[PDB]
Length: 301
Length: 301
Ligand SMILES: Cn1cnc(Cn2c(=O)nc(Nc3cc4cn(C)nc4cc3Cl)n(Cc3cc(F)c(F)cc3F)c2=O)n1
Ligand SMILES: Cn1cnc(Cn2c(=O)nc(Nc3cc4cn(C)nc4cc3Cl)n(Cc3cc(F)c(F)cc3F)c2=O)n1
Image (cartoon, rainbow over all chains, first blue to last red):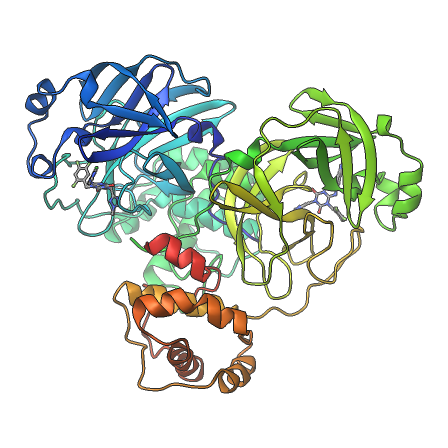
């Protein structure tokens, strides 16, 4: 039992968080070597926020218009540039806490840890997934703009998300570390809707394996399905397609539990068609889709 | 949007984790100033684990029998002692990463972050609550013994839990940092059952306040109750009775919403006696009991 969302230890990222201020507009930045990365929205006044022309706004700024603080210590800005929606401020000191790192762009269904920060100060850490509609269902308050998402492999931090905004529905939108949005969003304070979301099938199946590993098996059956027939039903219920690569990735969980991937698909099909009849799985009344196969193996070994 | 389990940033604790080995028995320790704290179980060989005589096992050990490692760097042990179920190994180097810290003993219902560690290496962080039966529904594998639980207030780390063992039901038991077990458990490899658990009433009330803050308030009724009357009913539904301290910690939420604590108790009483009539609260048909009043204020404000 005890299977739960588990984040990566955040220390390597905490050592990189700073505050960036332009006028009275302020947010979080990420300090790696001698460069601070942050949302370019920081350059906007409250009027500019509504409909910014970023190239015009930026040409009207010099290095001295940017105040960067690492805790209480001011870092002097000696260059600036913009890459898509990300501002890069070159500073005159290298961050000694810089971890080994990469910038990566993730795919829908992939999970990451978020270090929520306020005015350059880390506040909390939790796991999220990239939704099929390219939103994230985060927990973020005012002042969180510029908080990052990441995975850690060995000692290497792969940064995948920089937080920009909350949409009217309460879900979140942001960019990769090259400043390209996930999804059809723009860095402007105007109401924006997302596309209709879908459920991440491969993750639901991973979580059903986690449930079996933890002794919860009521949902298993003896029905069988082909991959095609499973996918027909999945599509009907606004579930993402399950690919042969997904089947392959679920191989280790299948081996560990002795439940064939397609038999687990048959179980899921019946849950979609029948519902849960007031029962829970791993304490949940809903089918959970924010654990990847990797997440499950990592936590269960 | 919504509420989720959120951990504190783990960096301050990561910098204190070490590995402690005695013979082939190995687990995690906590390095603060020039002392490493770890479960005294480390001094057991396999043959000692069932019925250890700790005083006898310890008299036969010298400083030179303890291998304490920060990564692959050995820290030389210069003293050893036992305090309850914790071993304290004085080392010749003060940890430069020691945060401001306190040792605290928590009550049932209180939440904390767990930094799960293996062989002195942090692996993941998640939030947990102490159950009324003094177990935690954690996520731990073999090699996790000595992982710690903590809260961070300002820049001070309050350590509250040191993990020792997994019980037959898959829940977890451990000590405070003074080595006193939470609950009726002992540090021996014997099957030990937890007492029957109950629902954490103060946290359910915090959850209801969270729902009201978010405009979901169908369950507010025209009635009130005394604390005594409420407690007597609570017990009939396997809910914890409230203490005076519980009433007090609900004060900020009560003030924020203008809903008196006892009026909320009356609302909860109606839910216990009547059920939910097919309705949900914060999207769920189940009442959440692992968010404290502090957790609610942290996530809302
Ligand atoms: C509730 N919530 C959840 N996530 C967020 C993220 N977020 C944020 O923290 N701040 C925003 N706008 C700003 C206002 C400022 C006022 N001052 C003095 N300084 C400010 C700095 C910022 Cl960034 N926004 C809104 C927002 C941010 C963008 F980057 C963007 F492109 C469009 C937007 F509408 C925000 O969502 N808030
Ligand atoms: C599945 N699970 C979840 N939590 C735990 C924690 N846990 C643990 O990590 N290890 C334990 N026993 C050891 C065996 C060792 C073998 N080697 C080579 N070194 C070892 C060191 C330890 Cl600590 N235990 C069992 C256990 C540990 C105690 F501290 C105790 F007092 C009683 C116990 F039964 C364990 O639960 N495993």
